[PDB]
Image (cartoon, coloured by chain):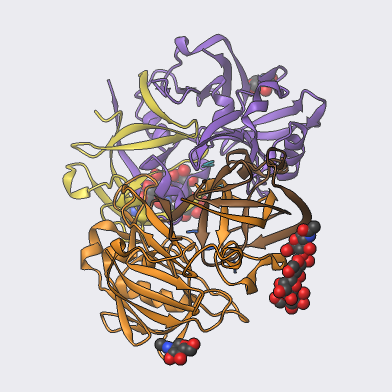
Chain colours: A brown, B blue, C orange, D purple, E yellow, F cyan
């Protein structure tokens, strides 16, 4: 500590930064959102209906030596949007150390 | 906007 | 140097319906509110970090730049406050409900004399919410008083030109008044271009049992440097520099 | 040289709500359909020009570029056709109802063997509608057959990689078929900031009286040069150049 | 005749050309819509509600020697949006000549 | 998207 995490500002409407999931790190951008408590990223196994991951970075467990599968379903609704998928386990590095 | 877990 | 939060559970998203997540610049979301509102009682990253004793102070702080063309765009500091981004000294408010970072608003007063939320109300401090949101008819009143116009679903636009003529809004938190001036609470955008400014107060009714709730988003944190303290469950504000 | 159609009545818009005219790149609309659907039964610009006898043939024609860079983006010719923009000889068919430029569709067939509108349906030829539209349910069927997934409200998307291998779709208009290859009916756009492909068919039901109707909009006209002949009340198509 | 009118292509979504209304002509870009039958452009008398005229061209009656008032109110609904105002009369030049 | 007079 203290760990500085530099955020990219988009139009003062979106502030996000880079983290890593997996060993070795796969880097994702996330918002550090104090209005919810779950971390998530697009899965490389996202359904064809999921237009959003086709243009975003996708996590692939098979490239991580530290992945532990879990598989329980999760579903979140935000004031802005809905998503669903399954839970997993891995190391998260902040920044993408 | 984007309002994040109602 | 980083932190390695290990053995963290997180969602692998497979379906994400509708426009919003296509349009967004971000891949995912890393939630930093209390464990209570977590889906599948999964332990949050900061919770997991305090638990592997990775930081000295269990606090994190956010500086968000209000200039879109500024390096850096802002800075999350994990485990301390970054002194270079705030002026004066933090004043802390106690978290009332430990689920979102909730706090008590004493009143919102508009300089022309309109007072909204008199007798107090509740507000969550949310970094992942862009605008300030408040219950629909109360924001409807605020928007007529500052003269913005309805756009679509609880969002109002104002000519960027008219901004210096607009009054300042003051949220009274813990006895202190925190001022937002018109350049603070209005936001420059583009559809076609220029002159299109949003009015940074969106109206949204969050229903019982959590709500009603006002949300102080990036518009307020963009002016006031926010410190979230898990050791003491208080949120502290100081004027960003 | 230009024309000057004098003593034309037009509206002056004082209220226009919605994102639509905010975003729209254009200042207004000059309608070129039949007086039968004119609001306040105003005599329409082409009818006034016609009356004033300013063009030798009461026909007007559209050429539309399908390449976003390519200048000129299109060409309207008032009072004649332009031979460098189409190839072949024009194929005409008559207007079935004089309100929109309404014409009879014999049937629409997706090559795989999905035949929509087998038994014939009605279509309007419309330069003001970007995509092709047809009845919701019928278009859904068409969409699933070429593997496009829903975005919101009858708009569909295809992962751009697949465009290159989809089936051609044929609209049989007046005996012969007009063929839309995959690259013809898909539009490469940039939502968020990325290469996405819109399916060029959206589903939307038009209520009777006027509905239910297929709308052959710019996607079609972008491949087949269209002539609107007020003198004979017939529409004319040719493959563009 | 024949009068060629050059259109601009915007994303293969919007095709629009320039016309002039007024003597001397005021230049407006418009879609030549075979799906409707009315011509309209924003008025300088547009309400502050009409966010559309904050950024489009507005017709100013006082600067036209050929303007004839009319005042009747119209209302039009397109598949994509509605609008309203009052009718007026003047000279239309295709193109802005 | 744009579909013009219903
Ligand atoms: C896959 O990950 C899952 C999600 O983390 C694992 O299941 C979870 O395991 C945790 C372990 O701590 C359980 O949480 C603990 O148990 C309760 C929390 O649950 C209760 O919370 C609400 C109120 O908040 C309460 O009213 C309900 O009765 C819940 O039972 C606490 O006592 C502990 O401090 C802690 O929070 C979760 O309950 C459990 N979640 C789910 C959805 O099952 C799962 O075991 C993992 N499997 C593998 C292979 O990794
Ligand atoms: C403001 O402008 C208006 C538009 O010019 C002026 O009146 C209209 O002028 C048109 C000619 O351009 C008239 O001529 C015909 O009108 C019929 C429709 O209206 C008549 O028929 C209907 C049938 O639905 C009947 O019920 C009405 O009472 C009318 O008798 C059209 O079918 C023809 O195509 C043709 O255009 C219009 O009648 C006339 N009406 C309207 C509502 O505009 C208007 O007088 C001008 N006002 C001022 C103050 O200058
Ligand atoms: C906040 O809470 C503490 C106990 O946790 C209390 O003693 C303190 O006086 C409170 N301060 C304010 C500003 O409410
Ligand atoms: C078009 O018009 C003529 C005369 O009105 C008619 O006899 C002819 O058969 C029509 N042809 C078609 C293909 O509609």
**Quadrant holding ligand 4?**
top right
Position of residue E87 relative to residue D123, above or below, is below
The residue under the point 61% across, 41% down is A24
**Looking at the picture, how far across and down is residue D236, in whole percent?**
57, 20
C235 horizontally vs C87: left or right: right
Please state which of residues D226 and C12 is positioned toward the viewer in this rendering: C12
Q: Quadrant of the N terminus of chain E?
A: top left
Which residue lies most toward the bottom here? C119
Residue ranking furthest to the top: D88
Task: Tell which residue pokes out farthest to the right in this image.
Answer: D113
The image position of residue A57, as x and y in percent, is 59, 41
Q: Establish if C197 lies above or below A45.
A: below
Q: Quadrant of the C terminus of chain E?
A: top left
Q: Is residue A66 above or below residue D71?
A: below
Q: Nearer the viewer, residue D12 or D54?
A: D12
Instruction: Name the quadrant containing residue D202.
Output: top right
Q: In the image, what residue occupies the spot 29% across and 52% down?
A: C195
Residue E76 location (% of width, % of height): 47, 51
Rendered residue at 34%/57% (across/down) = C65
Residue D155: in sight, yes or no? no
* Residue C184 shown left or right of residue C211 in the figure: left
């Amino acid at each position: 500590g203290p760990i500085p995490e530099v955020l990219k500002n988009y139009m003062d409407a979106q502030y996000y930064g880079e983290i890593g999931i997996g060993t070795p790190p796969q880097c994702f951008t996330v918002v550090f959102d104090t209005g919810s408590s779950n971390l998530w990223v697009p899965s490389i196994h996202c359904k064809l209906l999921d237009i959003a991951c086709w243009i975003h970075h996708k996590y692939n467990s098979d490239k991580s030596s530290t992945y532990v599968k879990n598989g329980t379903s999760f579903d979140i609704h935000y004031g802005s949007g809905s998503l669903s998928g399954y839970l997993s386990q891995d190391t998260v590095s902040v920044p993408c150390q | 906007x984007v309002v994040x877990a109602x | 140097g980083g932190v390695k939060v290990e053995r963290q559970v997180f969602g692998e998203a497979t379906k994400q319906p509708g426009i919003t997540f296509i349009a967004a610049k971000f891949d995912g979301i890393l939630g930093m509110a209390y464990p209570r509102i977590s889906v599948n009682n999964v332990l949050p990253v900061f919770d997991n970090l305090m638990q592997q004793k990775l930081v000295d102070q269990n606090i994190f702080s956010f500086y968000l730049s209000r200039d879109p063309d500024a390096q850096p765009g802002g800075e999350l500091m994990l485990g301390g406050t970054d002194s270079k981004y705030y002026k004066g000294s933090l004043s802390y408010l106690n978290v009332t409900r430990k689920a979102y970072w909730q706090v008590h608003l004493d009143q919102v007063e508009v300089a022309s004399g309109l007072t909204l939320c008199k007798e107090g109300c509740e507000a969550i401090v949310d970094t992942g919410t862009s605008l300030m949101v408040g219950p629909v008819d109360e924001v409807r009143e605020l928007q007529k008083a500052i003269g913005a116009v309805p756009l679509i679903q609880g969002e109002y636009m104002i000519p960027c030109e008219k901004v210096s003529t607009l009054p300042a809004i003051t949220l009274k938190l813990g006895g202190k008044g925190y001022k937002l001036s018109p350049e603070d609470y209005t936001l420059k955008v583009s559809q076609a271009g220029k002159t299109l400014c949003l009015s940074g107060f969106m109206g949204m009714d969050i229903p019982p049992p959590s709500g009603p709730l006002w949300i102080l988003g990036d518009v307020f944190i963009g002016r006031y440097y926010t410190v979230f303290d898990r050791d003491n469950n208080r949120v502290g504000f100081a004027e960003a520099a």
